[PDB]
Image (cartoon, rainbow over all chains, first blue to last red; front, side, top):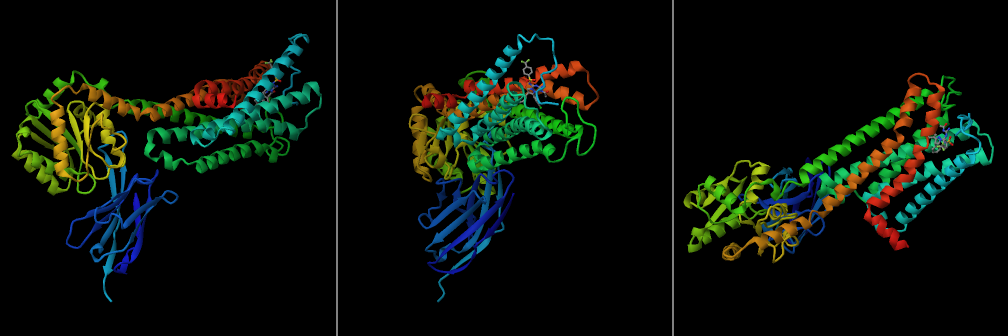
Length: 123
Length: 478
Ligand SMILES: CC(=O)NC(=N)/N=C(/NS(=O)(=O)c1ccc(C(F)(F)F)cc1)N1C[C@H](c2ccccc2)C(c2ccc(Cl)cc2)=N1
């Protein structure tokens, strides 16, 4: 499949953003969607995950601040964050997992291009 | 050149003409009444009409109405009233029946697609197949069938084109007849192949994670597996999945293993860790594998049957996942009789109960180690009750697939009944298209034309006998 990402950009500390990621699959596209983050000089970390409805998962560092939602009309995922911090500056990636039912060990993962998010306390 | 011309076959005495007429009226009226009853039951039950999986019924009955009422009407304007029929009204009468047949075939096609999506792509069924989408698809199919049936009325007859036309069907060009026969034949063949493929794949796939495919007993299988891995008998724990941070807690499992390695119980404990991922976690797992003789790490690709054998040999399965939306690993392990020590998060909470496994706090290596120690202590006594409970709980989640396969089998039965009913008529129509005829073929065609009404009779019987939901709704209305 293919994933198109949008919404990254610079913002003041304490603001709020919303990134969007659209998938192009054959049947339902991805079964699981997720948002990953990579800070400069740091290992890639999963920041949010969703399957459908209230089946979301949030990292302990974004619990209560971030919110992940999914729309099946366009088969896309949104990630909306409020009360941003300078620690949140990183490159965000959109991940899509298509997993098999007849064999739980089989899965396929697809990644996006990644978008920069810079929270700056400049005044 | 009248529709349902009974002037032929003067063999029967006029004495039984009344008997034939009354039988025809009774059959037509019974078909109309039962089709109306089925439609009313479907429309007046909110549970039934909101399910796309049953929408085909609401189509088929309507088709069964279209081919029935017209027949009764087409019998009124010939026998009791001798009103001769012109070209346009006769073409409309034939178009009704052709539209009914095409709508039946299209409804079977859409039902086959829905069954494939429901059975072989379950994780998408609640999203790909929605009620508005099903309604739109059925409406589009009905419009296509109506257009195909109406095409001769819009200037595709053998008078406006001035071309040779059929003998059994006057005022109807043979080219349109051949086109319609080809379309319905190829569609029916594709539907038959699709249903056969769906049923075969469902049979081979759904009944896979079962104990009946393994030879021996639990103890000997575990002993043989440990001997193949060069380890002595002991309580065996199994982890299978992804080597990563954030999704599956293989790092949590490794920390718990390191914590437990400092105790005296680690001597009576075996660990298997299967998966592939980042080089760092794989290196950590291999270092633990070489440090401890009771730890085995597999990174290669494992066949489905080998994983099935592993599930049916180990004692416990550890699932310390941070985010598990479906928990298919737990489902397979419980189907093959393995007590799961899983994290209480996501889809693992509703699958595993306190009597069918152990639940652990996510992301706590110490709590996971304590739960593993608790499982080891519990393993001292008998464990067959836990295995039976796990099997029952896992099979409780496979009911929907079995109902879907039953619905698919019902659809296959409906399709084969339709094929038997509409076979000889289409064969005679092809013989018309390819070559000429004698009066005997016309007579047998006129005699076999009632199989359509028999099909419209027997379809509601199949719907009532097969589906329990329709019976429940019918008794509710009573
Ligand atoms: C083409 C032709 O000539 N049909 C014809 N002559 N007679 C027909 N019935 S009957 O003659 O009244 C008739 C003949 C024999 C018996 C009995 F009791 F001995 F069994 C009872 C009644 N039908 C019925 C069928 C039909 C008609 C309308 C709606 C549903 C079914 C039909 C037909 C079927 C397919 C298509 Cl494509 C076109 C027409 N034709």
